[PDB]
Amino acid sequence: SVGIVYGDQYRQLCCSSPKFGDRYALVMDLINAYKLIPELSRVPPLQWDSPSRMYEAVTAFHSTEYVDALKKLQMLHCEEKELTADDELLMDSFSLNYDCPGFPSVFDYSLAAVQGSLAAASALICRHCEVVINWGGGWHHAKRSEASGFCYLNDIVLAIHRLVSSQTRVLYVDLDLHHGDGVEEAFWYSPRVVTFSVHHASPGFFPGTGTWNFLNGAGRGRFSAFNLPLEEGINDLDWSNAIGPILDSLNIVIQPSYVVVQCGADCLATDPHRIFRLTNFYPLSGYLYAIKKILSWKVPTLILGGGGYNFPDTARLWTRVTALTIEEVKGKKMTISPEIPEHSYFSRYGPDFELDIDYFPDSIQKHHRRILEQLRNYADLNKLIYDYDQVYQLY
Ligand SMILES: CCCCCC(=O)N(O)[C@H]1CC(=O)N(c2ccc(Cl)cc2)C1=O
Ligand SMILES: [K+]
Ligand SMILES: [K+]
Ligand SMILES: [Zn+2]
């Protein structure tokens, strides 16, 4: 069973932010336009018995003072009440400013992603679903006491905490254009959550981490945080060859109980960032290559969204990821028309109204040797036994 998180209230909240507007509606409506919803099990967002239960859940990671501030920000924006100088200073102390400003539903909006991803984790734990998709989740930058990169609450960290707290190891794979710093930091000292981010890094590029400083964890979590920074311009094939052996080696050595994949769509060639040149093509899209490989491991998996600022092309990609997941999990052939079906947001898919995006297409060897060494160090530190040459052969 492949699950997907949605709901009427969830849709309105996921569409209430100024930065991401109606992206989630385009995504879910295109999935619906392609007749995928009857193939999927709807997973409703988690709700709580009381304010105290909600607060307990969110402060499993975030600080009480930060959650207090995020609630107050919504309350202030809920009225005409412009912030006092003291309130501005309070918000600044949590980076609830500039790129992460307040809006009338900022706490409800960020809490909704947490509700969705926690529900997804529970459905995996109870084995109701083999894979769960949450295209309203994936906010990998939020820190314990700091908003960052349009992320206010870290739904990923809270979902992973629910998985490991259910011997359990989690592999987190972050495919976003940006380094998954918030998730990496949360599990820096934890050997049982191994994090792996592939991303662009360059001077002045957000958030700045995930590159040479390589730090890789600390304490009992030493060697447990993996990173592969790539230069601008990389295409589907080169990105696939860069991460492919790393993914397979992580699965062999870690033997994870769960995999959590952040599938931010800002690596697409048509994203306004214009840094990587990945596609959604399925003849092959780097995203689909990676997701297909992860799903072949037959490990219960959470697939999350993230970045993606070209909303129709994000919808194009995530619709294909959803169909691929159905096909790989259920063994059911999926046939998506190359033409965008008529539906509410059909006019947004100009100019050609095709499902393919409108695009025409040894430093990594050193990184591979470095990561192989780090994997061996992780395995030694943690008394894990693994076929050294079967893993080296992957590269
Ligand atoms: C969780 C994924 C979506 C939101 C975060 C993310 O992964 N995004 O896609 C980037 C895009 C971008 O340009 N930023 C950014 C740049 C500079 C500054 Cl200062 C703050 C934010 C992000 O956070
Ligand atoms: K990433
Ligand atoms: K870790
Ligand atoms: Zn991003």
Image: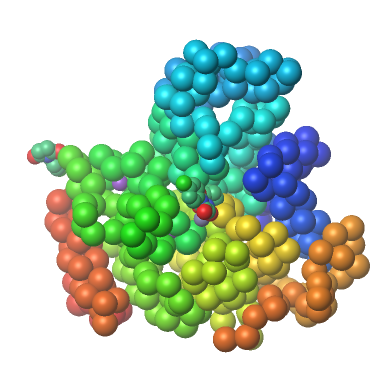
Q: Is residue 16 above or below residue 284?
A: above
Q: Is residue 311 above or below residue 99?
A: below
Count all numbered tags in the image, as a single digit. Answer: 0
Is any part of residue 296 visible from this angle? no
Q: Is residue 390 above or below residue 38?
A: below
- Residue drawn at 49 percent across, 71 percent down: 276
- Residue drawn at 46 percent across, 26 percent down: 92
- Residue drawn at 49 percent across, 69 percent down: 275
Residue 203: x %, y % from top left: 33, 59
Q: Nearer the viewer, residue 104 or 131?
A: 104
Is any part of residue 341 visible from this angle? yes
Q: Nearer the viewer, residue 258 or 161?
A: 161
> For this view, does 35 lie left or right of residue 229?
right
> For this view, does 393 lie left or right of residue 146?
left
Residue 78: x %, y % from top left: 71, 20
Quarter of the image for residue 314 reads bottom right
> For this view, does 299 lie left or right of residue 169?
right
Residue 235: x %, y % from top left: 49, 79
- Residue drawn at 38 percent across, 72 percent down: 231
Q: Nearer the viewer, residue 254 or 285?
A: 285
Q: Is residue 142 above or below residue 55?
A: below
Quarter of the image for residue 192 reads top left
Q: Which residue appears farthest toward the front when viewing the image?
A: 85
Residue 76: x %, y % from top left: 65, 18
Quarter of the image containing the N terminus?
A: bottom right
Quarter of the image containing the C terminus?
A: bottom left
